Amino acid sequence: ACPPPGLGFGGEYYSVVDGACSRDGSFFGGKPVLAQAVGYAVVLGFGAFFALFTSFLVWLEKRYVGKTGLIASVIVSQWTWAATILQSSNVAWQYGVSGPFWYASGATIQVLLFGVMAIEIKRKAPKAHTVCEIVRARWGRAAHAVFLAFCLATNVIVTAMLLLGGSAVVNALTAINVYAASFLIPLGVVVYTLAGGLKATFLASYIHSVVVHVVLVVFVFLVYTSGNRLGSPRVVHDHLTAVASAVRNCSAPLSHPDQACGPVHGNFKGSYLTMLSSGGLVFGIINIVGNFGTVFVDNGYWMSAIAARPSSTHKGYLLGGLVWFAVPFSLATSLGLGALALDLPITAAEAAKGLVPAATATALMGKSGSVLLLIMLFMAVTSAGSAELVAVSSLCTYDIYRTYINPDATGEQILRVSRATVLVFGCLMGVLAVILNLVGVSLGWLYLAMGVIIGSAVIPIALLLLWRKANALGAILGAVSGCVLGVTVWLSVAKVQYGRVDLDSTGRNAPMLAGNLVSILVGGAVHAACSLAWPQHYDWESKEERLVHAKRWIIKWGVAFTAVIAVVWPVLSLPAGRYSAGYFTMWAVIAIAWGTVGSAVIIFLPLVESWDTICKVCEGMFTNNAVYERLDEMNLRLKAIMGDMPEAEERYQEMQKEK
Amino acid sequence: ACPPPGLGFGGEYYSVVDGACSRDGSFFGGKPVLAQAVGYAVVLGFGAFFALFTSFLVWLEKRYVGIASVIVSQWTWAATILQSSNVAWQYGVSGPFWYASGATIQVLLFGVMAIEIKRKAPKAHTVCEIVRARWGRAAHAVFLAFCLATNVIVTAMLLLGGSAVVNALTAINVYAASFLIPLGVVVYTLAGGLKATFLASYIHSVVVHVVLVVFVFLVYTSGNRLGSPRVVHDHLTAVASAVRNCSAPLSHPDQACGPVHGNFKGSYLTMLSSGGLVFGIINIVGNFGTVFVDNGYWMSAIAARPSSTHKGYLLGGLVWFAVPFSLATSLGLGALALDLPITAAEAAKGLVPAATATALMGKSGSVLLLIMLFMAVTSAGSAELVAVSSLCTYDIYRTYINPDATGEQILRVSRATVLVFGCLMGVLAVILNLVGVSLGWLYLAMGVIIGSAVIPIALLLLWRKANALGAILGAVSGCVLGVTVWLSVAKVQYGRVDLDSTGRNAPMLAGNLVSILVGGAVHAACSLAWPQHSAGYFTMWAVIAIAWGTVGSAVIIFLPLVESWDTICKVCEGMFTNNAVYERLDEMNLRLKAIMGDMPEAEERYQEMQKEK
């Protein structure tokens, strides 16, 4: 009997050789699950396929036709990319229930912050088109290359993250060359971003939201409610308290030292259910800082804020954070600590590239749901990778070509410059994800190492539009007194704590907490010092009564779902220890309810707010009412010409009554 | 299954009956592979299927509306699919390079021919008219007879190759599949209204080039059975290696096993090969005859439009240089590298590309090959019938039977000739079927009967002196002496004269060269007398073959679409939208507005009617 007592869950992964039936060495090192043909269709024929459908809908709603419920969809479409499905489900594997809660407790605050800066941009700089323009203007000439460099480095980092995770899963599921599946990703995205327009559209975001939010409910209901394997979330409690049980022995070849076994280190008493994880709050602050270099440096978020009117949509985006909270909670608790319950043979190196969801999906459903994950992730990568190409293209066409090459540029000269920039950046990004694959850098290592490179530019940019002193000398003297002084400490703490300096030691948990806290607390502390000595006293020159109301509903009610969700809830949940069978069964119901009162507003509210358009389009796709109205309106004209002319009236009457 | 040592890929091919650890007699040894019903629906139901679809597509163009592909339609017939991957099988890699050596020569010669035929006399409709125009009246029965003989030979080749494949794959009767193909073909050439439309050529090229890539990707890259330039390489060196287990029981002396004469040390990768070289000169001799003595190309050049025509010449020449290489190399190296029994006589009939299609991928493969051949057989046979009709009605009726020609008699005689010739060649393709001879013998005999008078035709349109007596003397002398040499060299040095005893390399090359050179020299002499005035190499080969394939079926399949995007967008509108109704309803509304205005009272009294609504 190879399955030892107390573990009858996973038997398909225990094979017997020469006795003792050594545990499997990995999960995806075996034969491919799906055919190699489908991977080629998904990599190449997905961005193009999602473009002609969008243009078809545009043609329909333009041919026949000519509010605080749809902005909640563009918020989700913007905030979701290939680190909510993958990275949120890795920290759940590593630590437990503290993973998929701290991920959503730091990535939602940045939703609330977005909107305060949207107000300060419609009444302080409504003619920017970028973020460096509200920086050249102001500050000087030297303060236009440091911030341009940081803004472009952020785009590079996010694109590298979305390519390194979109290929490491298609390789595992379809057995394609990870180098061949890496260069081909930034061609479908380029096809999509050049086929259907070039800017953001309120219709594509809705489709992205509905696809993601349907796959979400499928997975959550399969894991918890409907299922003959792991449904009825009482089995999960026993399953994952058996793995952490101290009676289980994990030594010799029963469990390799790179997998999940025995008690978990850093928690209280040893459990995947406690909220007392030291591997918790450490992925707290680190994440929070990381979710400031994306909403305050990346030009995509600024462009989204500019392209949205806040006069009547100041309330909508607060609904874009309370529905997006279910995306990394209902998915990283179902496909997260659902791989722990079934005792999968997942390796730490395999979990760092974003392969935990690809294991639970291929185990619970096999060939019938390993396709759903690909569709979800590749809608999330083709809708977020197309937001970074536009950002860098708009940045280059407005900050290096139209202001340092030829100011006398016509409206036709800058229309192919942008297209060429998109194409060249897409090709160059495919010649960075092949090198990054052969050095061994994964999505997990790069996600945490984002607040050290970028993060010295968060406070200087934030104070650019809040309080009107903003000393120019110090914004560039704090961005370079930050980043380098951050990397120095991050590699020095890693220097004398493990010995050598490499990928496995510089990014464990300790060096990267010291880097993300010294690269943002210095860039903003030394800048404030120079700002109190030579205040420039900017005059903000180089309906107001309605707009001042905007910074009262998002700042007073703004802090009502940032402390209830992140401050009082954890401290109230602390006095629970290991979750009892009746207490975890409430946590699961909260997780399900957030996703059902979740993906039932974004799918239906925009439909009922635009019913007068979907009715008009059908009135014309099927019926022929237009022909009838024209024939009526030209019949009445003959009636008019005939009314005053009396001789023809009698003749027509007799010609008609003889029919 | 008994595998000999060193042959793991050699599986069920080696039999185990009474032990006898040896291969079977033939791949197609009397075991049906395809359903017998599909073959009847392909032989008959395909000629009358590509015609009504073309008429549909052309009817749409005339209801809503009001050059590099023509170099493929007349060439991809049953000579480059059914024999290129026969010389590839017989001599390895050197074959599908010497075979596609006249591919460029053909297209350049045809370009020169067109640019000269427009400039000298742009109203001929035949070459049998110009032959009287320049030379004497008596030089007319010669260059009519040779043209008819060439047409007969090419029709026979395209019928004897398409019957064997359907006899093998579908198990249709070999005699009942030889009298029915030139019935679907004649149905097609009558339903299409004769003529040479450009719409059919594009669809032909599209189907050929979509089947090509499907077959190539199954061999080199996307293959779970055979793929990559190294699995093919080590199978190639394993099939022909120093160790030779196949002497008495294994691989009967007419199969493929053991080093072959010619190729250096029996290596199926070199170029120094007598067999590869001889089918060089012979292929060139044949291609000169099928372009100068044939009449299909003379008629095809009448369409002209020289600039785009020569652009198409170059582009389609590159494309149809690519296509032979890719398909022939793929199928021949699949048949060689993979253990597969082919009789020495079963390759000459053109079944080698049929064996690698039903084994590499199977059932779904076979039908593809079938259509890929049966789209290419009812596209050159119809051209040949149209050519012979145009050559006979304009040359025996218009000038000999009745000098007068009403506009309706021409169509009478044209369709009469097509109908008679489409059936009279079904009995010459069934009488030659039970008497031995297959595609291999005709493809080499074509250079003896034809090509006796090929230089005379070249000098008629191009060279000033061009005496009339030289043409007749050269033609008769070349023909008679070529026949004598062909039937004499097979007696001495080879013993008896038989069907297979005359179709070797030296006896046919001798006949071809004697047929050409003496005729050319005699014509010139009389005209001057009376001037009336390893692993890396194969990897590079595979890479460049795929490169030709990609610079192949990607410039004639998509470029015409973007070139004519306006027309393909105008028809689609006319189709799923009713913009046509609005375009005139609004105009009537504007006219009614025009009549009003000049009438004061009606203008106001009409308004309250709208206000009522």
Image: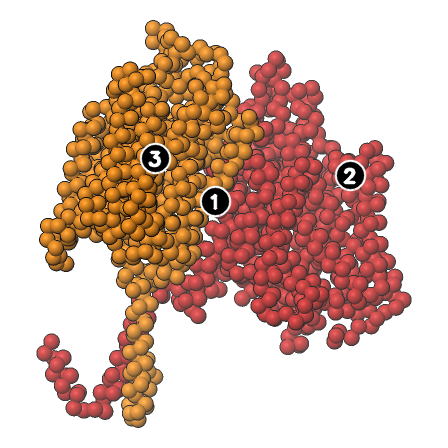
Chain colours: A red, B orange
* Residue B347 appears in the figure: no
Q: Mark 3 lies on which chain?
A: B
Q: Do labels 1 and 2 share a chain?
A: no
Quadrant for residue B359, please give it.
top left
Q: Give x and y (percent) for residue A412.
A: 57, 68
- The residue closer to the viewer here, A646 or B115, is B115
> The residue under label 3 is which amino acid type?
Leu
- The residue closer to the viewer here, B241 or B102, is B102
Closest to the camera, between mark 3 and mark 1, is: 3
Q: Give x and y (percent) for residue A236.
A: 58, 34
Instruction: Tell me: B234 left or right of B44.
Output: right
Pointer 1 residue: B551
Residue at the far right: name it.
Answer: A533
Q: Quadrant of the C terminus of chain A?
A: bottom left
Per the rendering, the mark at residue B517 is 3
* Residue A56 appears in the figure: yes
> The residue under label 1 is which amino acid type?
Val
Label 1 crowding class (10 Å Cα cut-off): few <14, some 14-19, many 20+?
some
Residue at x 72% of width, y 44% of height = A448
Residue at the far bottom: name it.
Answer: B600
Q: Mark 1 lies on which chain?
A: B
